[PDB]
Length: 154
Image 1 (spheres, rainbow, N blue to C red):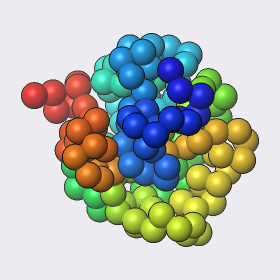
Image 2 (image 1 turned 90 degrees about the vertical axis):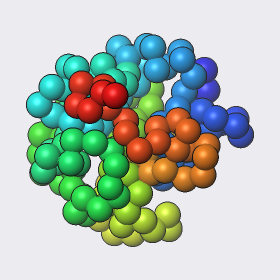
Image 3 (image 1 turned 45 degrees about the vertical axis):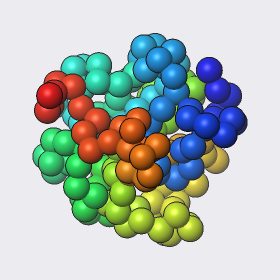
Image 4 (image 1 turned 45 degrees about the horizontal axis):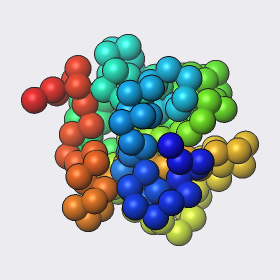
């Protein structure tokens, strides 16, 4: 495993919004070793797609497929329920969202205001906080255009 993604290769290339990785270890864990943020309806199944997904508030689950990079700013966060499940299961190990490239953060990687404060707060409490996106064959190789199991499947 990696302590807050310290290495260089995979499981250590997630800054603000690159992708989702953490060896089969984490990908298998999905209990009390991490805290994702995606979907809402089938929070159970969709969570299965990853470790422990959170009930995020999006329009149609980000088009029910992490493949678009467009969803409105703070599309899934500044609402209520989102922070509810998170703050509830916060402090597990690592927090990761699936807003994708250019969506909830608009693709800034610098320190915007909306998501800029949302992330800053998520890390302030004591976390790395990183979302998905689709950069290079690496980040996309991990969670390319998809990131789903009971929403899109194959």
